[PDB]
Length: 156
Length: 51
Length: 184
Image (cartoon, rainbow over all chains, first blue to last red; front, side, top):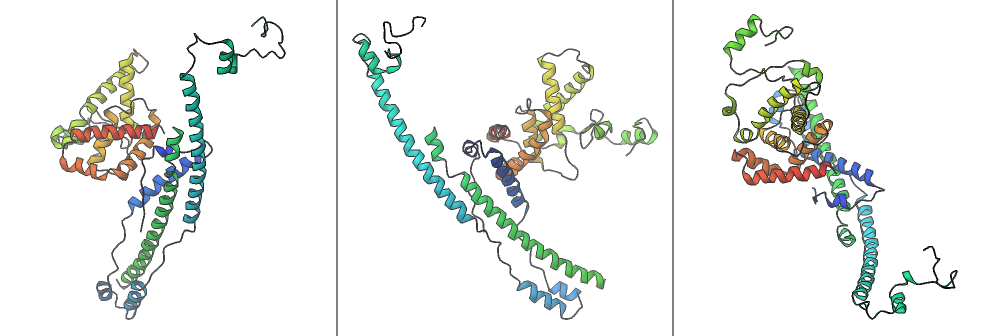
């Protein structure tokens, strides 16, 4: 009763942090070993026959006793109580990843705004010094702590 | 590229999910194999004692 | 048949080598040196040769035998570093890597299709510069990979006989992907 979803294990490497890279290696190698351990087991052996073991074992009562106590023996699947935590933590990291998504959308929109500004620039033939300081303030003479002419220190 | 890594965020958690599912199914199959082993032991012991 | 002190020239080994044609020679110094099973090799010969192989193993493992012959003789005269060009270090690299390919644990035989896959991963590139102590973990993870999601392709290899050209480029792609996952 297995529900399996195999991934290509490249995005598993692209998806992990530096903080949990060793634990991701441990979980990856343990999952590889556990998939191989699944693959080594066939699904079930056949049921224990009772005509042959009833004819062999002459101990009366014992063969029908073991037949009744074995063929009417059922044991449940060992439970989990962890899938709910895994799915809720999945939903929480998806919600944090969605707010990270919308913040990156605003960031790339501001990038595109600056780029469409910068392609549509004065072609430097009509450019004044004041408009060149307006288009970027990297090169503005500050005139504070250098308030005299020229407004850089001379050695620069 | 960070958008592309945002899109792929349903793979790690799927690896944890099917890891837990495979571990539990292997454990139940080990229950099955184990009780088969001990009832096998009982019947073979009775047969060898009779022999 | 066992000899005593490796003396092949004794009466019973000369008689029983003379009657048989195939013979597998173990010298023992490779058993204590590290390869298992300890075929020390060039003394061993099978006279029926490629006629008793599958078509895939014949397509892959003849250049391996010729390369091991080249490797043995160049290591034998360049024990001390006689002349090391790029060709001699290529020969020693491919020879040492195939030497660690031929190591195999006790009581673990594998089928022919996994052998074609792993000697394909060893002879057709993709392992020549990969740190010869790491060949055994490469073996384990490679067999785990191919038994994990490549069972029908191995069925194609063992039932079709020859390793087909689509299967050839597919083995190339899978060993390249696994080289990435091995340097991952």
